[PDB]
Image (cartoon, coloured by chain):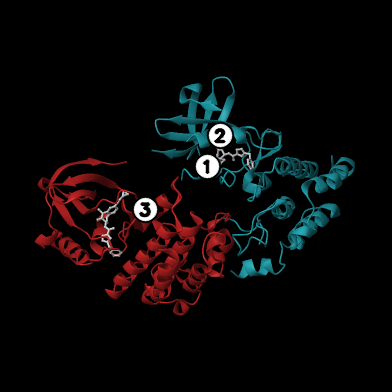
Chain colours: A red, B cyan
Amino acid sequence: LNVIKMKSSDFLESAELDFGKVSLAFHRTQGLMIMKTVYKGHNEALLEEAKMMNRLRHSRVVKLLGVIIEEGKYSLVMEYMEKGNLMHVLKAEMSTPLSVKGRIILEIIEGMAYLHGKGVIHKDLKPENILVDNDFHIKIADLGLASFKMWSKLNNGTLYYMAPEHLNDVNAKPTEKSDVYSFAVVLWAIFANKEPYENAIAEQQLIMAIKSGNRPDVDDITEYCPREIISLMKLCWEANPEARPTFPGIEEKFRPFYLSQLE
Amino acid sequence: IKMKSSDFLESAELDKVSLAFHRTQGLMIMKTVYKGNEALLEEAKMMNRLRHSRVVKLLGVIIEEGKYSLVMEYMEKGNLMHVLKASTPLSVKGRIILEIIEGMAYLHGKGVIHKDLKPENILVDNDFHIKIADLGLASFKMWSKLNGTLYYMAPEHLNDVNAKPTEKSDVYSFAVVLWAIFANKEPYQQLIMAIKSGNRPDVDDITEYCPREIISLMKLCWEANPEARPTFPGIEEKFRPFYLSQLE
Ligand SMILES: CN1C(=O)[C@@H](NC(=O)c2nnc(Cc3ccccc3)[nH]2)COc2ccc(C#CC3CC3)cc21
Ligand SMILES: CN1C(=O)[C@@H](NC(=O)c2nnc(Cc3ccccc3)[nH]2)COc2ccc(C#CC3CC3)cc21
């Protein structure tokens, strides 16, 4: 457990930011980190959960660096991703070029393939959980703590990326195909530079529409997105979960396309 | 367009909104949208330019210490369905329909498609005149960004959230409002597919007297094919002489 134990004295300084009690801190040897804190006023179960998450080690997946438990105040600690999340970057003034968007897609695929390979279902894949560093590499995060059972309980949601089978039944068993659907909508957003379903009027309209087969508007991306990716996102958002490909399957389809046409 | 909290003498919370008494311009409804940019002011100014007697006027905005609020006209009797369930004379129901037509024709003339026309967005003043509102911020794009009845939604939008709304989308919603005005009640997955297949509010459940012309109008305006529906100027051309000779 010492592998994930951090102390306030390990950091030179920290300050609260304007979710929840999030702060930016400089670690004495490991650099800038983001800290999320909850006040409670049992700890060993929290530390083991942190140790488990810390074993998810892959270049495109957020590595939990450690936790701090002091004075009834409980913190998770991770590396600071300066450019924020994927949608923040997509909407930036600088228009992200095709070669970069293609690499982002491939890195998302790599990260999700690793997670599923480790038996991890994400359950809330979405642009907000795809973080971007200063060289435009990405890492997959779980900022809503959907996979942190204990740490989520201590703290006591867009539907655009949620698979239709989970619309109105969020307690159904999570599946790998649930994540593949989310990925399909992320693909669309990467080329649209925006959230889907802008012409929806009511939440009930949208939920029923998606369950009936409605999908993001492909006509918004045809002049930017290559045909191969449009075909890919259609496979990945098929209504039948078992008709959706695996992420290793997606990777074997997408990587040679990226290499010859995009890189 | 820009107001300050100091511009108001008194305020009391009203069943995230409050009724406030302005120093010079009188009673207003205030809603704090966000607690915690120039595009917001520009959008507010464009809404302020939507000046018509049957359309709610955005009176101003308050931007103070990270607190963002919209300020609009005060409509004493609440929304249309509240009034319908209160009894409204036929000549007043006819005038209300005509005032909906006027306000919607104005909005369409300005290029504004409402997209969520319904009794809750039709506000009634002390003298039973109406104004059209957008309480769900369907047209307030930038202010909505600071942060669900399907009975009135046209079938071309049911199960297709990507189709662009048009003037005829609002005409369908108007037809169902007509039914509600004389039924005095709200209408009606299984329902959605039924509506998309041609099911409509049951005219036979209107129990009070309703002119044939109004029965025919609501059937015309809720045609499944949007091109079979009239425009609001087309509706006014037919309805105003009817109101003037038979109802006023
Ligand atoms: C400090 N912090 C963390 O360490 C988070 N960790 C993770 O997201 C994560 N860890 N390991 C993984 C890898 C994985 C991915 C999917 C499923 C399973 C595993 N993610 C959890 O709590 C936080 C919440 C929000 C923020 C923020 C912020 C910005 C807005 C200001 C920061 C954290
Ligand atoms: C203060 N306030 C506002 O100003 C609203 N504005 C409007 O609806 C509007 N403004 N100008 C127009 C005219 C138009 C109509 C259609 C399309 C485009 C324009 N509507 C928007 O936010 C609110 C939400 C809810 C309430 C409440 C309440 C009590 C009654 C239950 C109040 C507001």
Q: Amino acid at mark 3?
A: Asn
Residue A79 rendering spot, x and y as whole percentages: 23, 53
> Element at badge 1?
helix
Label 2 near label 1: C-beta < 8 Å? yes
> Element at badge 3?
loop
In the displayed structure, B23 sits above or below A249; it is above
Instruction: Answer with left or right where residue A189 lies relative to residue B208.
Output: left
Q: Given this view, does label 2 or label 3 mark the residue nearer the observer? A: 3
In the displayed structure, B229 sits above or below A23; it is below
The alpha-carbon separation of the residues under discs 1 and 2 comes to 9 Å
The alpha-carbon separation of the residues under discs 2 and 3 comes to 28 Å
Q: Are marks 1 and 2 on the same chain?
A: yes
The alpha-carbon separation of the residues under discs 1 and 3 comes to 21 Å
Residue B10 rendering spot, x and y as whole percentages: 49, 25
Residue B129 rendering spot, x and y as whole percentages: 71, 37
| Along the line of sight, the residue nearer the viewer: A97 or A27 | A97
Badge 3, how many Cα within 10 Å: few under 14, some, many 20+? many
User: Seen from this angle, which residue lies furthest right?
Assistant: B245
Quarter of the picture for ligand 2? Answer: top right
| Along the line of sight, the residue nearer the viewer: B227 or B239 | B227
- The numbered mark 3 sits on a residue in which chain? A
Labels 1 and 2: the sequence-earlier one? 2
In the displayed structure, A259 sits above or below A2; it is below
Q: Amino acid at mark 1?
A: Met
The residue pinned by badge 1 equals B142
User: Seen from this angle, which residue lies furthest bottom?
Assistant: A242
User: Seen from this angle, which residue lies furthest front?
Assistant: A260
- The numbered mark 2 sits on a residue in which chain? B
**Residue at 46% of width from left, 22% of height from top?**
B6
What number is the disc on residue B42? 2
